[PDB]
Each structure stands twice: as C-alpha cells, then as structure tokens.
Amino acid sequence: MQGVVKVNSALNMRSGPGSNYGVIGTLRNNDKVEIIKEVDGWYEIRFNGKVGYASKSYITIVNEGSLEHHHHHH
C-alpha cells in the first residue's frame, strides 16, 4: 500500500485527525508515504519516523482494489 499526496504547493501534517491539533510538519507534492490505517475519514501516515494524519482531499489511494487493465476512457 502506498499513498500519494497531491498539493499545488505543500500540505501540512497533523498529529491528530483534525485541524485543531495544528501543523507538526510540512509535506511536499508527489511525496510517497506509508498508510497505516484510515480513521474518521482521515488517513494515518508515517514520515521521518513521525506519525500523524493527512486530509483525504489532498491524499489519493493507489490501487484501491483496482483490477482494470489497459483501460481506456471514452
């Protein structure tokens, strides 16, 4: 499992799953991270030996049980 962060500039990381906790670090775009689990819609990721949560809007799950091959749109 590998999560991908998509942000125009940079996405802030938080110790708890909420904006109330506050930013504990800064994440860059195209930054591969390891997802531990999803709680309250928030994704648990680990970076630099630190554990926190990130917004699902800026995080896209890779291979979410996909199986389609050589798929073509329209």
Image: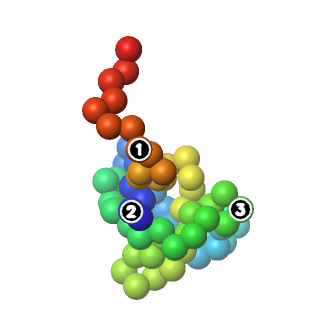
Residue 17: percent from the left, percent from the top? 65, 67
Could you tell me which quadrant the N terminus lies in? bottom left
Q: Is residue 24 left or right of residue 48?
A: right
Density class for disc 3 (Cα within 10 Å; few <14, some 14-19, many ≥20) is few
The outermost residue toward the top is 74
Q: Please tell me which of labels 1 and 2 falls first in the chain.
A: 2
Residue at (61, 65) in percent of width and height: 38
- Which amino acid type corresponds to the residue marked 1 in the rendered image? Leu
Nearer to us of marks 3 and 1 is 1
Residue at (44, 45) in percent of width and height: 66
**Separation of marks 3 and 2 at Cα, in angstroms:** 19 Å
Q: Is residue 53 left or right of residue 25?
A: right
Q: Is residue 45 left or right of residue 22?
A: left
For mark 3, what is the residue? 40
For mark 2, what is the residue? 2
Q: Please tell me which of labels 3 and 1 falls first in the chain.
A: 3
Nearer to us of marks 3 and 2 is 2
